[PDB]
Image (cartoon, rainbow over all chains, first blue to last red; front, side, top):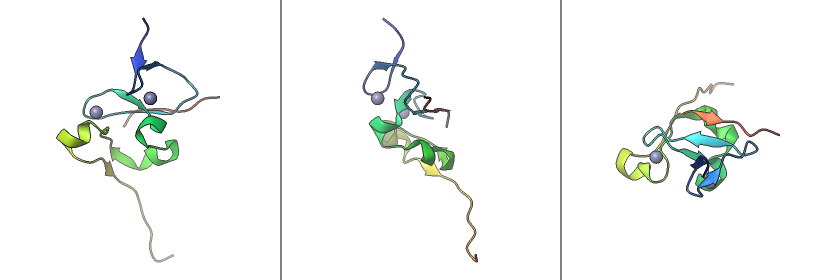
Length: 68
Length: 8
Ligand SMILES: [Zn+2]
Ligand SMILES: [Zn+2]
């Protein structure tokens, strides 16, 4: 056996974006849990779908300008 | 969060 990850329990494939849940510290493919790689810089706290129930929804944090 | 970027 080898290290496996995510809800799909697969070995690490370097061609796939992955994100680590801040609550359980496990790794998930963005495509398996609905997170796109381009969205990750805006995530302040990521909770996977399981951990959302015990720890609450993920939090986004980003900068914004409004007048222009 | 920690991430692993998609590679080629
Ligand atoms: Zn997966
Ligand atoms: Zn989790």
